[PDB]
Length: 572
Ligand SMILES: [Zn+2]
Ligand SMILES: [Zn+2]
Ligand SMILES: [Zn+2]
Image 1 (cartoon, rainbow, N blue to C red):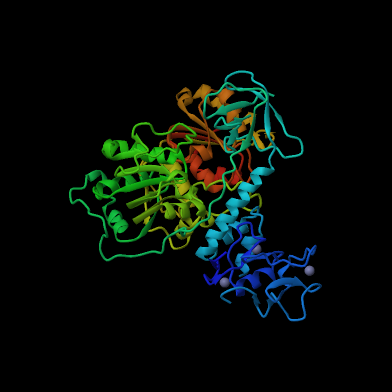
Image 2: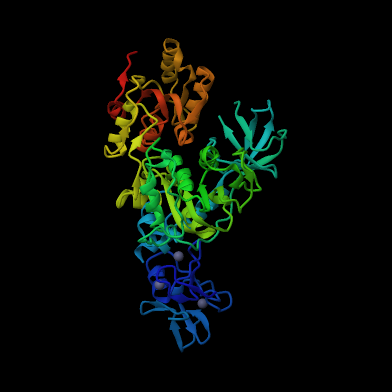
């Protein structure tokens, strides 16, 4: 009942009962809230409701303090005070942006813009509210009941009537009922269980709706600059492998937090692990939102750090297969590799947060709350893909609005930029350098002369919403016969349904752009599939073409991005 004001920190008893996160508001702010919004319920110790029997006036603007209780205009005694008057709501210890956060449904881009341009306390309010809204939306979906079981990796389902049916992608992770998490892919559909279990007819699933905890720690701790490297002890014998990164490693030690923008294949993992060899006594916790990102940092550490002081932290409710070569769940090892949602409450000399484009402000806050550290290092690239915002359907979320770190990176610039791509043939580096990196990304490799573009709109069919372009797969099939070296290619498209069809027709291994992020392949085949806002997204496009080490074939739908590709055009 006692708390501080989410806007101005002022002590109050007043919470908003109409906000989904019931924030503590001061007398001055609670007034400015209730008088501007449909939010009229105010809670102190006792709710601001008419105490008169059978009266249902709950609106604070229609209520009065009658002695020691609260009454409406129809029930107030002669000596009574309006709870709402003179710019204040009556309470103990006696806002435009807060209002918009409190009352938005989080389906508009402008909602995410505001949640990232506001004050720091409003960013935590925004993040809590958003995640609460996202979770409470997950209740509105319909139960999937198994009608039959075809085989080991295929079945049919019976859906609840009335409640909408959620899009069948690997994105939407269910829970089985108490038989661990389950995911679905395009009447023969494909059942994929994180735990091997004999599919039962009658058993049913529901989306993993975890309860949103309150946020205490900021997204970003306040910045501190030091005159000397603080609480870290550098070697003077530093392997020539990591000589390039010495000045940036010293920058890391002379600031509380630091931001690294690394375009694809510019040496982010190398930088992160090389920080451990430069401060060799320092305890480092390596963290990222996904298991794949953490497993990429584990692989690079296996190559350079002693396997005895490494621990891969695995949440007891083990979802998908991950890194199996460290000691598991040893929190006290010098090197700890853990997803954000599984971080223990510990301390560190250095925390490295990797794949920062994919972090939400919720994730940025949780990390500050679970890890107290001398130095925080934010590694990723605002020109790559963000976390999916399941509720956002109107407007596109720009990179400066992904999270606080990306906002800093896109406004004041990053502290440290990795300027040289070592992965991609120059055709790809030159294309994305001009597209998303203001020409500051440089090619190490020569042009491969194995980067092809073909402008072929084909025919777009839809599996519900997820798109298919069979003619674009037909053009690939034809190219593969004439280019049999490309049979080792990973097939990449912005749609699971396109990937499902290309898997069956081409036999190539298959990846969505979004699941390709962080990975590299010698040869990539990319079918754009459609020219939608999703397939033409410059960040998604950037990721798609920078997966390739040697060659890439791009079958394009969008004239704009086709023309920007500095690739040899094919005919047919
Ligand atoms: Zn206030
Ligand atoms: Zn409210
Ligand atoms: Zn009344």
